[PDB]
Length: 471
Ligand code: NA
Image (cartoon, rainbow, N blue to C red; front, top):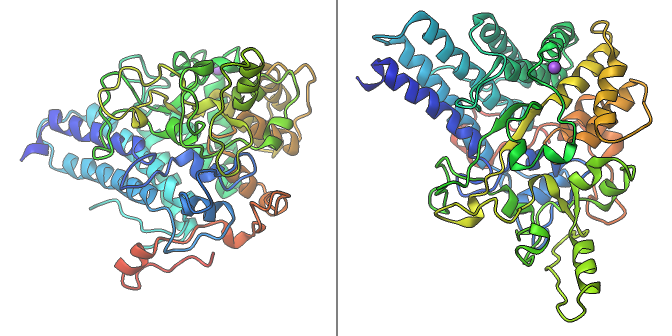
């Protein structure tokens, strides 16, 4: 009865977006979607009390995940998203008073969201259940369903290129273009490279997408939905009431609590404390040139801050509590900043206002450079690469080789859930992700590690329906 009117179907479309903001704290797990890939690359450690604190993260990082000790929150969030998208398509088949223009717009949002949620399970697990109404496909078969759905959304021709202040967070054409380029490039689907390049060029031609001149302004609260932002997942502290017992409410994010220094003295250098997950590797700080603005915007030297403080006051000496894999560096982009939870009305730990940046225009420029270099089309790959390189303060221009473009991504997107997928899709993962001199990673990546083990509870529930990955 209820989901028969346009007004109520709009409420269902809004509901289909909610699982976007769940995985950082949902289904009694912390599975923040960016960190779940970055812990498997070469930029961060895992941290916590020990290798048994969030053990599933430590196992994934060392390519020894097991089905009975695996992340499961993200899986449940992805399929909750898929189910809510399917509900809207079902409701539209039984719709009283929905105009043709509105039907197509509602459809464009939920089909694009559905591909976005399938992309989470496609990337992490590959060979997973598929449904468009409320069965295990191969990764290659799921790619086929995903890319065809994006083609249909693009062909509806109803999404705006950019949203306005009232609706930031809604699906846009630019968001769909970026998701299209993402899955096309991860699949190595050279048949679609020229189309993906044409889409990147359309975003580049828009005067309403560009680089922020100062990379240090991006991850500030004032940098949310800037000229650089193509897509973010919205989080707020203002009267936010996300809680241990209320993880699903539209509130703040847990991410800053997870990755800020344990028992930091709150307010020192306008940073707050967290649980000491995902310290930034010393090697990440060292790979930057001194005049690369990304170095300090990525790597916050918490220990140097206290060393300075203690020199300037030998009376009032401070420390934080170093945890497993401590380096003295934390991920500045999503660090707990004094004031960024100040208006929350529940658990301070779960209500940070930091939006999760998904697609930034520097990714558009690097995607276009790489696609041009791979022979998708003619275009100024060198200009596109160096707009990003030079925005970071670097004076030397670099040639648009594949290695140079892949390394610029590496410098550009630490902690943003890009590097692991870039290593795998370019064939670099086997040679880069090898045992370290710390004894932290003790295994080498190999092609069997591309798809994680499916959770044992899902294998058990499918009654032989779900074939476990050979990981
Ligand atoms: Na532009």
